[PDB]
Length: 429
Ligand SMILES: CCCCCCCC/C=C\CCCCCCCC(=O)OC[C@H](O)CO
Image 1 (cartoon, rainbow, N blue to C red):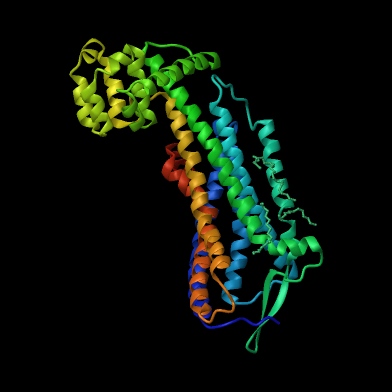
Image 2: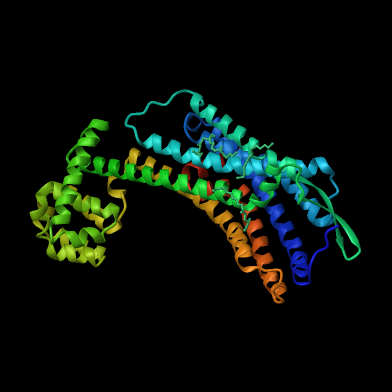
């Protein structure tokens, strides 16, 4: 017997009973089709199976089992407005949900780490089949996620609510827990979800994504100079010596009064083109392009490109000048685009896409919960208008978190052309 409070939330709960039902059906249809297709695509392709993309298959299977189990039960619960499944199902569904969120966050972390290790080596030789250590990684990811979900199976049980005469059974984390550790988990449930299942995955993925993109940049500027110098060879020793020459060059840029303001203005890609000109003719020579450097600082790419075209540097070496100038105008690596640079652009866009989708889907829920414990008080007479506002955001946050179970296959379709052809070929079959 636990009666509810006032008026405001009742009309909103009824309004969202239809919204949540629509979102649940969309996530179910889009999720069971996208994740099943993605699982088939990853494993059947031998060139993705022997790499870090097998972790995306683990991510897809984790969402897939969450879709088929949690979504239909939650739809039945919303429509019936009562829990009619018994005690066993009241413990299974939260356990399945908690394990799925753990599989998602641990597969995302392992993918960003493996993608960093993949770009940290020259001439890496892939094996045949799933790597043995990646298999241990996936097993451990699922083992840890199940163990961390055991409290949900222990704590959840059915209670009876008294709504001014009407009795309705509710499945929730029981306020009275049997053991001291289990009662502590009831108080720190939301903080534990925010710390381990949001702050930890974001901190690790963004850290290794930064390391991966920095390493991609030092290799792109490496191949950029070797292409412009006619050719060369890669390797850790060759890159280490080349990075020292680049670091010594930028130290001369930052001491030069003419090149310091324009270099700080440019982005990482356009800074590589300025470094290229320094490698070719020295800093005293690059500082002579006073008009062009001013236009680059004012971010007039077309005007600076035209002004650089009418120069002795352009006439003597047209081919190299056109590529360096194109890099200034576009700000991309299109003039030096090869199989290596195109591979790194594909990797960087997919990893950044999955992490961003995960962060945007779970940000409203946690943001709505911090507003509940920093702005709400039971005493205040004006709580029902404020409670009315807080419940809307929490419902929005619950729906946004459910969309993450179907957003990953769609996200890869729009960002990656490699997966887009794989999705079309799979559904054309
Ligand atoms: C009782 C309190 C327990 C609190 C929780 C502690 C145990 C789970 C944490 C890390 C296990 C990660 C290893 C499992 C396999 C995943 C490999 C991986 O990629 O880990 C990502 C990141 O390093 C992970 O911190």
